[PDB]
Amino acid sequence: PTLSRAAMEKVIRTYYDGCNEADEAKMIACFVPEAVHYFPAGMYGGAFRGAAQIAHRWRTAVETLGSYWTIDALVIDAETAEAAIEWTHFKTNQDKVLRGAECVEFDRASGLIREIRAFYASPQAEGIARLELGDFDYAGRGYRVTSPRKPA
Amino acid sequence: GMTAPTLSRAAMEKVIRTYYDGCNEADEAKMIACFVPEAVHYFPAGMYGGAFRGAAQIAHRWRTAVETLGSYWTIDALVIDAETAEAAIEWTHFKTNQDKVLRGAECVEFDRASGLIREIRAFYASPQAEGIARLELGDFDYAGRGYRVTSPRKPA
Ligand SMILES: [Cl-]
Ligand SMILES: [Cl-]
Ligand SMILES: [Cl-]
Ligand SMILES: [Cl-]
């Protein structure tokens, strides 16, 4: 089914408002129940599995870190039911700032978020052979895992 | 007055794919043709000494990467927004000759007046660097571009 750019924008903005408000019910309503949030490998212990887990993690972040998130850019593709968000995570209580971007997939039937894959404005970690999302099934999802180029 | 051109989704996709082709082909001319001359590529602070200023510089530096690292890039997801004339790309940078893989995502802005890329802002699937107060893009004028600089929870 069709999902408009405006409908996706509304879900995304409601979600980030829910984050900033530490309002779990509000956040949960923006996702299909089994939604998964992925992050760079070596973060949060791995993926957040389920809308309730995602919401609890963000509530905890606000309470512990004083987290506040801004939507700095929002790219929405109504043809593919996907979006990308450039964001800032202000860890207020620590006087720290983390910026990044994330890809968002919607479930067309419900018009809700089914997956988020986040990336950071953080330099490549030294000595790590594979810098990719933690717990993400790259091979099963059809991503290349080995370079197409013949090694020198 | 003026009317901002609406670029088609196909047009934006064509430029992006030509760009990535040019990257893999180490073809500076092909890459340069995908950008306005003054285009800037941003990266996480600490990477590549800062931003790449100008199409010719982006092209030269990726040509160097192919030659020295065996770099090969793939487009893993492509999100195109004809309302804003912007795109986002989930990508993989295979540093072939080092047997290393770096994945990430980037925001791409188009110049509507030419149909070419004016800016790329790239982010990585790399963990947060320890003890760095601000993890943000190198050389990017957050303040001047209207981005928040300090937490909205702090009175302003
Ligand atoms: Cl493969
Ligand atoms: Cl179109
Ligand atoms: Cl500010
Ligand atoms: Cl701050």
Image (tube, coloured by chain):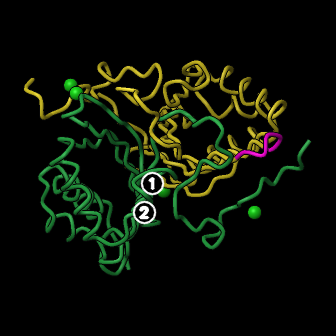
Chain colours: A green, B yellow
Find residue B94 and report its horizontal and vertical position in percent.
73, 46
Compare residues B22 and B1 and report the one nearer the observer: B22
Label 2 and label 1: CA atoms lie apart by 6 Å
Q: Please check the rendered image and state whether residue B153 is part of the magenta-colored stretch, yes or no.
A: no
Check residue A47 in the rendering and tell me which mark sits there, or answer none: 2
Compare residues B15 and A127 and report the one nearer the observer: A127
The picture quadrant for ligand 4 comes to top left
Q: Is residue A46 above or below residue A119?
A: below
Judging from the image, mark 2 belongs to the subunit labelled A
Residue depicted at x 45% and y 41%: A120
Mark 1 residue crowding within 10 angstroms, few (<14) / some (14–19) / many (20+): many
Q: Are marks 2 and 1 on the same chain?
A: yes
Give, as a three-letter code, the residue at label 1.
Answer: Phe
Please say if the residues under marks 2 and 1 sit with CB atoms less than 8 Å apart: yes
Find residue B141 and report its horizontal and vertical position in percent.
38, 20
Q: Is residue B27 left or right of residue A112?
A: right
Is label 1 in a helix, a strand or a loop?
Answer: loop
The span picked out in magenta is B96-100
Instruction: Kindly identify which residue carries mark 1.
Output: A39
Is residue A77 visible to us here? no
Give, as a three-letter code, the residue at label 2.
Answer: Ala
> Given the current orientation, which residue lies at the most extreme right position?
A152
Quadrant of the drawing holding the C terminus of chain B: top left
Q: Is residue A68 left or right of residue B7?
A: left
